[PDB]
Amino acid sequence: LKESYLEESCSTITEGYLSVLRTGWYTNVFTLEVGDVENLTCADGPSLIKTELDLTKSALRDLRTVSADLGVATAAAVTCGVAIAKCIRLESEVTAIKNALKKTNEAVSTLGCGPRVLATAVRELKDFVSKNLTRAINKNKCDIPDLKMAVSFSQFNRRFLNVVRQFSDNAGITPAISLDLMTDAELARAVSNMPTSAGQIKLMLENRAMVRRKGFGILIGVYGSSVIYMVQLPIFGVIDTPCWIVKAAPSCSEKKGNYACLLREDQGWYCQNAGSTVYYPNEKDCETRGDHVFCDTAAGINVAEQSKECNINISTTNYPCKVSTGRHPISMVALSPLGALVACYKGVSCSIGSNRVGIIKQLNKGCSYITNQDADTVTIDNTVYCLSKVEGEQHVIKGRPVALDQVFESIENSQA
Amino acid sequence: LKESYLEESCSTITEGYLSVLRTGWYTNVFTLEVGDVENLTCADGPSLIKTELDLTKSALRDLRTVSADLGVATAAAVTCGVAIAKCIRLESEVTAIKNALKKTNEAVSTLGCGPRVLATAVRELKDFVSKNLTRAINKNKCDIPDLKMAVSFSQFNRRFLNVVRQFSDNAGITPAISLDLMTDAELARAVSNMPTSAGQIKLMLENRAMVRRKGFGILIGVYGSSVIYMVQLPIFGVIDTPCWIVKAAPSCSEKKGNYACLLREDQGWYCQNAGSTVYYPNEKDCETRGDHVFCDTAAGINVAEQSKECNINISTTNYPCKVSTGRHPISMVALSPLGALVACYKGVSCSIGSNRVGIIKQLNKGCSYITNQDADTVTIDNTVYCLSKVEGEQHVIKGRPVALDQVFESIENSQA
Amino acid sequence: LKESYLEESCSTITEGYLSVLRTGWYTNVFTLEVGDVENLTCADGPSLIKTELDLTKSALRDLRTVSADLGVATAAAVTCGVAIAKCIRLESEVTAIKNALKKTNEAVSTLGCGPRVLATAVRELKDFVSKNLTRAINKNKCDIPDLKMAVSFSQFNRRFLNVVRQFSDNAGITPAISLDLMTDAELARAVSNMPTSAGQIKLMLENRAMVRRKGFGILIGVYGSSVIYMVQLPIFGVIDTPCWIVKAAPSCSEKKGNYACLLREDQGWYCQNAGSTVYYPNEKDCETRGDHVFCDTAAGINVAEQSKECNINISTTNYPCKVSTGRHPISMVALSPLGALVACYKGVSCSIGSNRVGIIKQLNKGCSYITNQDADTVTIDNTVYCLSKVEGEQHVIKGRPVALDQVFESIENSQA
């Protein structure tokens, strides 16, 4: 909640973060009973209930014609998911978990390889198909005067049909959990049943939309009158360790109308997990929510603890800070948590504006750091960048503005 | 509508374009009245209307469990969008705009920070919930013999449920405007109310599907019986300035079975806006529609006016034309507006075919330029490239085929 | 089904593949009859059937307000698709194919430019609109006591409305075929009608979900009471030629706490088609299904047959094997078909685990090759990588671990 501007490097650092680290996967297997619906037929000619039965059977048979045979964390995670659809048909665990879920609509159970996985039953469609609807469909009569029967049917199989749309349209693995895959109460029962300490399950529950976004779904298959799928939910088994984030902007010097520029390439996320610092170089591997930060940890890299020497004595530091270099001039804005680093050079015009006072001042050629208490908006030409009004303490560390040590090594080698 | 082939560089230039430049964002805030639907309950056991009420209340409460806390133009644009959802709950402007939209279903109004934003009301669901439906749900009786009441209910809340699907499934920010977020008449009222000159609003209206594609949606929140969302629509405030587009293909020379190749890296879009030339290096930042070109301008870079010297005297030119170089042979086709540059080298076979005459001739090893009046199709091996039949005048500029001046500087440095 | 581990290069090769090569596009044009539905109006005030008619007419008119004007294979393919929507409105082939599909609901016919394209009719909505429904809507009376009429209407136009959602939401070109664009029976009739030999159509039919994923849809337009769209289905006209796939992992050597590392950059897919070897460098250009491999061939590059000399004598080989080089240490796992190459260096811990025995052993610093019969899982720190249990024969080829010859050329040039 305390941000430091490195005057010496035209850069920012943002501190004060709590990890929410994805360390594992929780499997919520759902079983949707459709019922013995294949052995029902409408022979009283064309009918609305007949059209719904033919639609239901066509979507079900279309799902029975379905068969299977990236940033790093997700690929290791998918290898997990495949492992669980496999061990499922294994030893017909179906038969086992089937016996286990007749008894109840929600239960915990160790799978052949599964370490006590979650099983949730949704049987409304079979009971309706079996009880109310199948008695009205005995004797092959569907143009019944009971129009109520047709409307209950299209409403109750709607969840299954959209479920079929969601599985047929995405070739078996949705990237997240829709409210039709798992409602919120079922989502909450599954999130609540995860194996971690109290603060982690409670915190994951709060922001359960992130559990939705970071999880995904796998088709297991159709067996008779049973619909089977599984949802992989990220277990954020690690919370409240230090994280901090690093931003940087181009440092350019001009002599005689010509430019020499350099830029730090160590932007992105850093976290202190298990005695090492993990770098999440891409934005998408981590995600902020207020003061808490959600990261998939398998997406990070163990880097040496050496990054604080990149702030204190960056030229003279022992680990070589990686940088790139350039020969022709640029201009841009890298927005920061409590401001913006604005590199505004000849050829562009930059300004800061206020939602209360209007444009305050055009901003200077060179590297400038602007605070989000200072301005409400920044503009470069016609590109508009507005800014947040979030509060916290900011600080300036005075100093004059391939591995960077390979740039010093390249210059130093060419002159002797 | 006049294309020039640069024989001297194996390259094309396409001229004759009218800008449609995204210069701003128009905010269309929608208010969907759901009604006082929470205080209705069905106590006459399980029912179709009860299931619809429980579904409606579950989707609404699921949306009440929703909370928040890339090519450059879009990120600056999102900072806008966040600014507007913030200033909305501010000073409960809700209460203000609420007072303002009771009076009418469509109106203009300055927001606390909003410079006269658009407000659109859609109240059908509350009035139905309140008038026809709530009187039939008094006294907690839902298995009524009026089946008409249940069908009007599922049809009228369908817009809200798909609206809920669209907001719950995308974690609050859709990338575009579906016909369920904003119908065409509401889309047209909002596009029509934008702040620019007549030719721009009329032209944006024509191709309003691009306004759909370039805009996006933000969830604001649920308050009581009111549903609130906002749609950011791009204001293409700039039209009919010169744009032109540059394509290039590999120029390869062979000696003794060995290749030396070079390629211009200045492909992409160029526009003359406000005294500078803006380069849109990625295709997606600009989009053609006939003779008009749609660009998001915040996606471009002010480059010096020096690019025409890259055509006249490219080796000797003063700004250094950026190029890359290579040592091992390749082969490819870069399709152009009125043809194709085909670099066809040893190892591949290339041909042009006609939909009328069939294969005309196999095309030559080397760099060839083919016109879309010349052929209907071009093939390299089994990769098929067909071509358009669009008309306009083509011209050949005769000439023998890191910054390119850094390639001349590198060769020139190594021999003395 | 026989995998070779190159001990000499810390690398894997997987052999035993059957091509399923996308060599062409099959066009399935669908014609959906909506009926003369515009000339029907409901004047008996507000009604459910009236709301459905107004919705249907609003979605239809919204689709009448729709107008148009990447990894390489797809872009050449889209130029195909555009060619076919063009030649369609040409010579009003509509009128021709219209005459041709009155006679039947499915037929083959050469288009003006089309080489005998497929036409499929779906007319249920017009016949219902015309026969049962239009007689009940004569005399402008929609609040009829027949509630059955309203439910048949919303069910029958549902396919058209979701069809409209799918076309309005994606700006006219879906990336694949939903079950609502083409049901499985229509999908099967179209796949079955493709121009190739028996083994190819039969095999494509098996895994028709890949035909779905690799095809896409194009809006042609609305004319009166006729809905028109086309689906481009990939014709995998080539099957059962040799393919093989190459993986590699970093080879690192340490001296005095310092690292020198190199890595082969020739990972990806290789196929023997038409006398040349085609390289599919990106995963997405090819896709495995068991022992068969699905590739879009226009996505590949003709490379010289020289790659087997990259295995036998890679340092001394004549074509220069492309490699990159590095100066600072890394650590990672590249999973393989029958195992994993695990480069585990100082700073990380790696292990293999078993679903039966538990963690077997922590894995060694250095380059290790682990078989999927050997372990069920591998872990680096907290990043979990599990593994498959697929069977086949593995083999080790003993040997001590820019173009690679440019790395030998760079070292060799700097010392003399």
Image: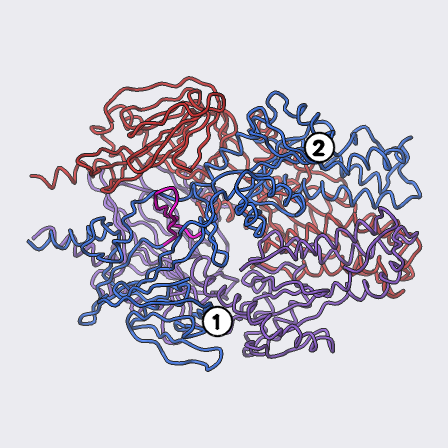
Chain colours: A purple, B red, C blue
Seen in the picture, residue A221 relative to B343 is either above or below; the reply is below
* Residue A300: quarter of image: bottom left
Residue A23 shows which numbered tag? 1
Q: Quadrant of the N terminus of chain B?
A: top left
Which residue corresponds to the image point at 45% horizontal and 81% vertical from the top-left?
Answer: C358
Side (left or right) of B100 relative to B178: right
Q: Position of residue B195 (x, y in %)?
A: 58, 32
Direction front: furthest residue: C198
- Picture residue at 23% right of the left edge, 28% below the top: B317
Residue type at tag 1:
Thr
**Residue B274 visible in rendering:** no
Q: Is residue A262 left or right of residue A163?
A: left
- Of the residues shown, which amino acid type is indicated by label 2? Arg
Residue at the farthest bottom position:
C357
Q: Residues within 10 Å of mark 2 (few under 14, many from 20)?
A: some
What segment carries the magenta color? C268-284
> Residue C23 or C156: which is nearer the viewer?
C23
Dot 2 falls on which chain? Answer: C
Query: Where is residue B225 drawn, in percent x and y?
Result: 75, 55
Is residue C397 or residue B186 the one in the foreground? C397
Left of A146 or right of it: where is B230?
A: left
Closest to the observer: B397 or A80?
A80
Q: How far apart are labels 1 and 2 at the CA level? A: 51 Å
**Is B111 located above or below residue A234 in the figure?**
above
Answer yes or no: are tags 1 and 2 on the same subunit: no
Label number found at residue C61:
2
Q: Secondary structure at mark 1?
A: loop
Name the residue at 79% across, 53% down: A53
| Magenta span contains residue A167 | no
